[PDB]
Amino acid sequence: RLNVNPTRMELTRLKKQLTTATRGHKLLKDKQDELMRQFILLIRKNNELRQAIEKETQTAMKDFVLAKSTVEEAFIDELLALPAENVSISVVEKNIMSVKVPLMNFQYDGYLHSNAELDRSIDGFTQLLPKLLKLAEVEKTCQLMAEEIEKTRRRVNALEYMTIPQLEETIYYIKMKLEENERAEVTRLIKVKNM
Amino acid sequence: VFSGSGLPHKELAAQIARQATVLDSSDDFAVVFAAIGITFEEAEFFMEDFRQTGAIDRSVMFMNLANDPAIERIATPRMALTAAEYLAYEKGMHVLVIMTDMTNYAEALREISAARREVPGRRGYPGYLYTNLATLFERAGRIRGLKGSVTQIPILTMPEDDKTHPIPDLTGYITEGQIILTRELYKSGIQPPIDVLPSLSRLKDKGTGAGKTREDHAATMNQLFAAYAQGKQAKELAVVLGESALSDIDKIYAKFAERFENEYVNQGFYTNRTITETLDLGWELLAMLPRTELKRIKDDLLDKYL
Amino acid sequence: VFSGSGLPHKELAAQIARQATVLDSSDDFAVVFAAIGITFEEAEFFMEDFRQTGAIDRSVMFMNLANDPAIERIATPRMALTAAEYLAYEKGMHVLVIMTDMTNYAEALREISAARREVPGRRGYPGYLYTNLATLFERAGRIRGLKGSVTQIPILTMPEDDKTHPIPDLTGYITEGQIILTRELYKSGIQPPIDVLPSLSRLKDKGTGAGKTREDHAATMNQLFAAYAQGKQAKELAVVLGESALSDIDKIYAKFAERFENEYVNQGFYTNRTITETLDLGWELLAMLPRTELKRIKDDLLDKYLP
Amino acid sequence: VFSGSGLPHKELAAQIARQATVLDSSDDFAVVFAAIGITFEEAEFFMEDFRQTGAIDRSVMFMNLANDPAIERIATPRMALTAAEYLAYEKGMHVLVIMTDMTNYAEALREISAARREVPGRRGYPGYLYTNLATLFERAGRIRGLKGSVTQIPI
Amino acid sequence: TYKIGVVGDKDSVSPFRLFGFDVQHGTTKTEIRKTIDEMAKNEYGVIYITEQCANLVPETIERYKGQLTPAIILIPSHQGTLGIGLEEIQNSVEKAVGQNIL
Amino acid sequence: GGDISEPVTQNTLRVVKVFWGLDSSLAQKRHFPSINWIQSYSLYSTEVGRYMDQILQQDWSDMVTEGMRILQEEEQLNEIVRLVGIDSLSDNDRLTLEVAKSIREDYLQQNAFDDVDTFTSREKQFNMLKVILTFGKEARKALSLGAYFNEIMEGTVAVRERISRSKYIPEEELAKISSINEEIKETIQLIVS
Amino acid sequence: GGDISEPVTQNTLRVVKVFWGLDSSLAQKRHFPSINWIQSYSLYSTEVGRYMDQILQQDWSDMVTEGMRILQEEEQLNEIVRLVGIDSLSDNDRLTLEVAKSIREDYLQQNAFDDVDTFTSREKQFNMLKVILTFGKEARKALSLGAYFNEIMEGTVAVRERISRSKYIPEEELAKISSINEEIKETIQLIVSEG
Amino acid sequence: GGDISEPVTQNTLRVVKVFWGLDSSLAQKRHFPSINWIQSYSLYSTEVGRYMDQILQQDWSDMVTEGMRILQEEEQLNEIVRLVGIDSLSDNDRLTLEVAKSIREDYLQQNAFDDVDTFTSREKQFNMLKVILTFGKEARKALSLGAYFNEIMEGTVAVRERISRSKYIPEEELAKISSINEEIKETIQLIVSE
């Protein structure tokens, strides 16, 4: 039960809130069910992409580790940060059922001695770049969706177990309270009329 | 007409009185207008608007103010109906009675009640409130073999706008349907603020159909009511899921409900539409819908009316 | 002080009696206590406190306990107030009237109007309950050309914790504000358990400001109310769903309402904060919010006090 | 037995009444069935189910209907318990008292109260609704030195 | 236009310097947590971090998981993976959908 | 008990044309004056609207109804804000709640003990109300071009703050109120680009 | 307001043996007669069912009981749908919903203004119910060995239409309803072999 | 209806310092005595706390303070459980719910018909509540040493029942309740290793 003024004004106000709560209850479960159906599709490519990325990235790394072992350390250190290329990101905001979803795209703006083996490892990181990007896009899409599913589900549980039952029980208490006092005052008025 | 304090039920009452008519010209139409517990300003508003439009020459007015004795307040509706029953059942006229405010009348009924030291009473109002309203409401209708009729449009205000109040509740038990004014609609700018969903006319089926109105009157009615219902529904899905999640058919319905409010019901208190103008406007809004969504109607009506 | 059964309105009334001294001066406070149908333990609490503080040699007390006849409660407050107005307006004293329980006064008054079989008002109470209460509470304040004053602090318990009950209702329309204790705050260990939102002071606007208090009194006050109100609203959304989903600003507001209740409000019944310390404490709470949110305070005050 | 409308408290009543017995002996057990303000159909169901199963041969029935005057509806359980107390305390029997419907009883008590210009209590029921019901139920129990007992099942 | 940052040991994430990525190497928990937090405040778009670094500072990562930016993505090192990132998938799946699709 | 169903209130509402309904929920937040802009009314608003429209030569009657409509939509929109998250709302609906937030805080709220904000003339009222509406009407434009709600929120934290302070500037500096107006259009103009 | 807690309704249900409660939620969506099939009851239902067990010499009481059992189960299934989602359908449970939906639409709903649906005799009432029930019987029996849910729903498109239109079948053409019943048996074997 | 808004209940609570709110829900769950530990209060709690601190010469006040605090946190935690689930809770929050559970089932719940459980002396109340709190303090400490909430439950199955039956321990054998404390420590520190 809620604690509020047991008045006629509050009663009429709470009853309309109950009507609001009930329709919004279903509006969330339609929202939840159809938010999760797409979540299944997204999380499947997430697992497919990550397991792909986590192996191409590893081999390219170990290849670089092995290749840099045969080359002089000082050479590698100065080769790095040539750059000579600058890569940045352009995030667009896409909506998937009232959820902010990132849309990422790549935006743009090597020493003569790069060994063949080193070059194989270097472009091996460049070969990786487009695939690491949508891994970032899909995962964040799934992360921002899973939290929304959590929030929706948790709000739904709150609506059904806490909000509405407290609302129904309060609309019942005040309604009966008003019915009691009216009986009391009327009864009092009966005796007065005899006087 | 069910209204509330602040709602434009006086502009609506005035609008009806001027625009109301029988479309057969071979029938003398009259309007008995009863003002009950009415403040001078809106009492003047009626009287002046009844003259500026020349509605007085067709109507009979009964003006009672709020500061005038409470017995006069009680007598005012019965004064208006006695006239209405004479003009109709003795002089063969089609009489339209408009009464406002009925809440003011009820308050005077309470005042005389405790004067006789009678005891309340559901929510303050005397136990015979039901009959006391019936005794002046039920005085209407058409009598067999008698030219003329008495039609009533009583207008009352809902205290804090709840239909569970004795005045609207008991009135619904005596009258066949009601017209509901909404503050939500009025605040948004819809004039007149008539909520079509909870409002009802139980006797509409008999006043429509070929010879009375057009043949498509009942079909367009059911379709507009349904389309608007699902139209308003698609809107509250677009606020929870965004417009992206809505199917292409529901987005049209969502746009339907919006324009159904801004054009169809938002006439303006000074905009008279004939029954034909109204019906054809219904088709313009039904044309908004996909053809695959218009298969519900008879194809006979679809062909003849857009 | 609007309270309820179980809430510590005793300690709150005792504290403000033990700590109230006006600035710009060092004058005394000749309090007058009026027990109205209260229990022995409630009455003894005040006396055992008045002796320890030495305020008993500075007071006059009218004792009507629960064992005393109920009808005597009708005359009891009129005795104390007459004594109070005497000491103030004739002997030139600064008087502090403390009456409890005011709820018991109204019920005793109902016993008569029910025995006389009068036409009853709301809830069985007489139709003159408002005026009768008004003949008590309005007997306070200062009068021209007189050094004496009478400050009134009546105490009542709200039946069923209901603010709309005839006794706390009618009292609220009379007195110049009210201080409301709440169970939700008390169970949370907040001492004193004062819900500042339904609380009120009607004479706080001319008794504050430069010359009275520090110049930033009014601004911080309204800014605190606005921040605490939205703070409560934020935590209201924090138990139904995770804190991360809501706006960080809302989350700062949520943390604000946490600090406000625990640090600002919960000072304990044995802490005496000067107006300097209470105001600077509020600035530290207002510190948590960006200056864009502080829409109640002028920019000049912001560049002078805010960290 | 706390029940509701449309629920089978009727069948539950008749079942117990015809199955009720003790492991004491063959004949020292009896049943006092009190019907209160119930419809005739409900009564005839009881009356004949007692006739069919032969449970009538060991039971006493007080059948009061819904159309019977209110005061006859409130006097019904008191005559049932009076007969039960006689059979149990004077004749040393183990008597089981079945009473239904108590809701009909309360409404009858409600009607009589208002007719006597009495001020009503909570939800329009007499203030002495507790005590009145207690003057029925507390009539059950065992007495020292006396063979037999009175057991009540208020439905 | 937003930015890209990379966190990991030298032998694994060094080549990312060739793309203009802000590539730093933290070994202590406080070092990684600070860098990530400053990256978020200076509006970095994506932060790729090795699982041997992400394992040291989990509390800060989940703090941004609900935010639009930055996106924090667990890449492996040359030695391999700890299987965190591919299990964090499972963590999000079961939190939403009770039974297994994987 | 604050219950406006009581006779004195209800009988008065049938004999008067203006109703300034005060509720405690606003008063507790120190929202002053605590007038419920949803349940309150004035049957003079039509004729008054035309009057103050004539002597100002500005579409005030259109401005006042669009401001009230926004507040009316806000009431219906808050119903789901209580249920679903605030961020989940549509971009063109989140702008409504912020432009309604502005009406409530920047305009509706008015402290009677502030010596500049105690009184507000028709021209200051106009300039203030003009700013609030023109912001939302300017932000909706950018929002229909493809700009994102959050992107135009951060870039307007400097101009919205000045709107919040538009209540506190003297009546000899109304030029400072319209200074904000053209600034808004200027600011969002290179945000969209 | 439709609140049966009314003193009149409450005192009435104390003496009446048959209760036909009309939901307002069924009033709109045009479910007529809007009698709520869960809250409503009949204290004659048992005896009537055995009387008609002799006038038709059929397990009519068994059909009525099964008809209700399908409806109560639907309500239990309905909240399962709400609290959790439409999945997992378990085929059998989602079928129970379709059979219940058939009962609600093809049997419970009848237009009092339709010239043949305003009245249906015991003769017609039996055949109509038997058709709906035998649809659920033959579908659940073929479901196990062995068909997936919308395989049946795809092959039973036209036959469920006949069941839905059995209401409007003239009394003197009562045999057509019986023809519907045995069309159902052949069509699910039509896709059982091969499916 | 158990509605304490009744005038009799209200009038009484104005002149008494102790309120034992009996809960119908607890009664249906066979939680006896059905006393609402959240709604009930005693305005003697502060004073009695001082008295028992000097009659036992222990820190009895802090024991009942942490004891209530655990119960009061349990309510906050339970509301979260019915929203997200019990497995969404961390090990600290799940430990609190298992300690609070013990407080209810092993201490609060007291059968009035059992020959030994119907009465519990002042010192047995101490030894029982001490054992209960001791488990919580040690398990919390165990978690800080890298141990998991699940491991604590499984490894302390034997002891946790001995705690559950301490209320059945005769007044003559109160030492059998004190010795539980040693077993609790020796068990959980072993779990940290194993």
Image (tube, coloured by chain):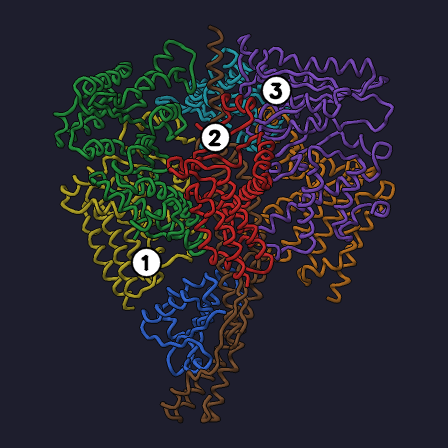
Chain colours: A brown, B purple, C green, D cyan, E blue, F red, G orange, H yellow
- Total tally of numbered discs in the picture: 3
Taking F150 as reference, is D2 above or below it?
A: above
Q: Position of residue B53 (x, y in %)?
A: 74, 26
Using the rendered image, report if marks 2 and 1 lie on a common chain: no
Which circle, 2 or 1, is nearer the viewer?
2
Query: Which mark is drawn over residue B38?
Result: 3
Tell me which amino acid carries mark 2.
Answer: Ile
- Identify the residue under disc 2: A174
Outermost residue on the front side: it is: F172
Within 10 Å of the Cα at label 1, are there few (<14), some (14-19), or many (20+) other Cα atoms? few
Tell me which amino acid carries mark 3.
Answer: Ile
User: For this view, does H70 lie left or right of residue D60?
Assistant: left
Using the rendered image, report if marks 1 and 3 lie on a common chain: no
Considering the numbered disc 3 on the image, is that residue within a helix, a strand or a loop? strand
Q: Nearer the viewer, residue D97 or C226?
A: C226
User: For this view, does H128 lie left or right of residue B143?
Assistant: left
What separation in Å lies between label 1 and label 3 (alpha carbons)? 81 Å
Within 10 Å of the Cα at label 3, are there few (<14), some (14-19), or many (20+) other Cα atoms? many
Q: Nearer the viewer, residue D153 or C28?
A: C28
Query: Which mark is drawn over residue E100?
Result: none
The subunit letter for the residue under badge 2 reads A
Considering the numbered disc 2 on the image, is that residue within a helix, a strand or a loop? helix
- The reply to whether dot 2 and dot 3 touch (C-beta < 8 Å) is no
What separation in Å lies between label 2 and label 3 (alpha carbons)? 34 Å
Taking C166 as reference, is C180 above or below it?
A: below
Examine the image and state in which quarter residue C207 appears: top left
- Identify the residue under disc 1: H157
